[PDB]
Image (cartoon, rainbow over all chains, first blue to last red):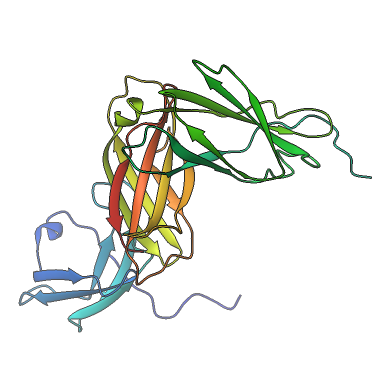
Length: 87
Length: 198
């Protein structure tokens, strides 16, 4: 009612930029049936890496998208979700 | 005042418990079913009638009263049994017929079976089936603590599904043996047996 949000996030779409990688290594370990630790080592970035986005889904599925934003200043993350053991 | 308005819709779902040595042609079959809900039992059920069917003794009906259990001795190679829920106005219209046949007990329908502990009281069971030649009505999953005598519980699974959710207070320290029994018109099929925790 008083105005717009002050701090806002900007996301650019660019196909050549979609060909630029920043993650060297990525691994996931199921800490529990709902908690999974995601570890990653990042390459030395030339373009400004604002943050990361982790997308998890059932493998070999069109839908089921679940995404979470991760700060670019960390190396390990805890993903909490009603994970399906079979999939 | 609640009085039975009509005849019951469908009969109860029942399974068998086997007692006796394998070498015995004659063995005790303990039929176990559940009481019918007001959706099926309508208002009240006065008794259950077990109508048998054999190639020699023909069809004879046995009343078990309100009991949901009935043990009968099976000797003939083929023996069909049907259960009807009789109320103040009549018996249950739709009734399941289950056939016992030792050769037909060697017919398998499940290609692969697996169980997964969704939670302490939730387990998902998945299965892939062989392409059936005999007429398959449904499946019957029997789960019990592995290497135990009693405590087994069974559920009727529709044959059209490939996954089933079983919600029971399983013992986490005890591994459970799951036995999925394919039910055919010709008789009970050969089960698929797996072992898994919960």
